[PDB]
Length: 86
RNA sequence: GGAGAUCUGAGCCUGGGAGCUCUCUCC
Image 1 (cartoon, chains in turn cyan, green):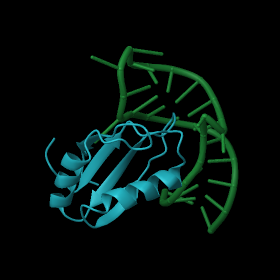
Image 2 (cartoon, rainbow, N blue to C red):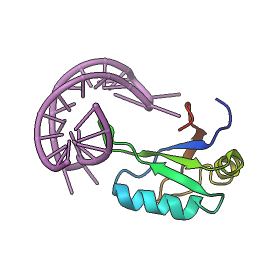
Image 3 (cartoon, rainbow, N blue to C red):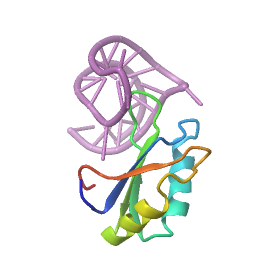
């Protein structure tokens, strides 16, 4: 995997509802750059992962570095570059 | 077809979870 516009965040707190996770993510990650969209996809079992698509790859890079392992709803975020740019 | 829905619909697969397929709702 290599840098791209989208970051993949797993290990989120599934106890939080979708909309509240999307807005918290937007408020914290918008600090690094303009965000085009945030996806919290529906999966077979409790959704605990999201995609944040920044407008500039530089924003995804600093975000990936700064917020790596940072507590988010009492759970440390595990951040990656998306396998496929979204 | 499109858009949504399960810690609050479901069966498989996985067995150190970015998997597949259904069902339902709306257009």
